[PDB]
Image (cartoon, rainbow, N blue to C red; front, side, top):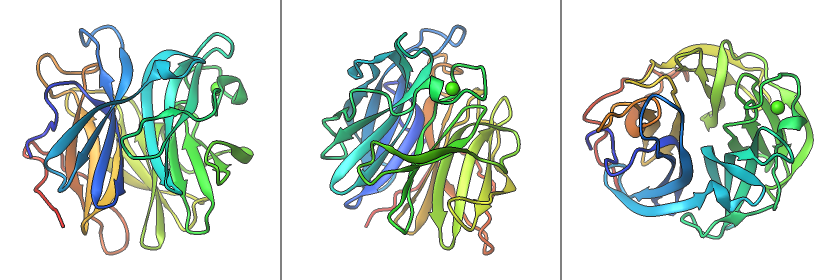
Length: 297
Ligand SMILES: [Ca+2]
C-alpha cells in the first residue's frame, strides 16, 4: 500500500476509529492552489478499510459550513462512537459573534453519517480560554472514554487543555484544566490507552515533530518520554492518529509528499506501523514509501 494512500485529492489531519471489524478514517481536504498562501479547507472526507490497505471512498462526510454559527475552515477533527451514535468534534472558524477558532460537535447514527450539528452552537468558544492572546488556540480536539465510563475532551494549540465530557457527549462537565508535562507543546493532542498506560502524543516545536508522554491515569501526571515522529516530508505540520487493529498498531499521519506540487497546504495522508517496547515506550516511527501490508480478519 504505497504511501500516500489517496491520490485523487489532497488530504490532511487524519483521525481514525474501529467499528464492527472495519477501520473508519477521517480527514480534512486541502483545496489550496499552492503551497505559498494558506490552508483552504471546506469539507471532511470519510474512508473505510477491511485490512488497512484497500480503502473505500465514502466521499464528504461533513462540510464546515454545515455549522450555522461557523464562518468556514474545516480544520482538525476526531470521531468517536458512544451508545450506537457517532460524535464528530471539529475545529472550525467561528462567525464574528464569538471571534476566533472554535470547537464544534456533529452527530451521526452510523460511521459514515449522515452528520448534523449536535448543538446548534460551539462546544468550545475562543472567549472561554483567555490565558493566551492568540485567536487560534482552541483547535485540534481529541476525545477519549476511560474504563470508568467518564469521557474527556482534550484540545489546544500553544495551550494544551482537557475537560470532562458528560455521557451525552455534547456538554462539558466541570472545569477546564491546563495540562502540565508536555515540553514544547504545539498542537495535535492524541490520547489513547495501551495495556495499563495512558498516552498523550502531540505536535511539538516548529516545524512540528510528534512527541509523547505517558501516564498511569488519564489525569496524568504526564511524563514526557521522547520523540514519536520525526518531522514529516515537505510539511511543517505533523498530525497523528494512533489505532489498534487486528493485533498490529497503526500510526496515521500526513506529509507534503503528494503530487502535483504537494506540500505545506496540499498535504496527503500516509500510514505506517507502530511498535511498543516491552516497558510500554513506543519505538520511534519510521516513515516509509511502501507503507503498510494488508491485515484483515
Ligand atoms: Ca482562546
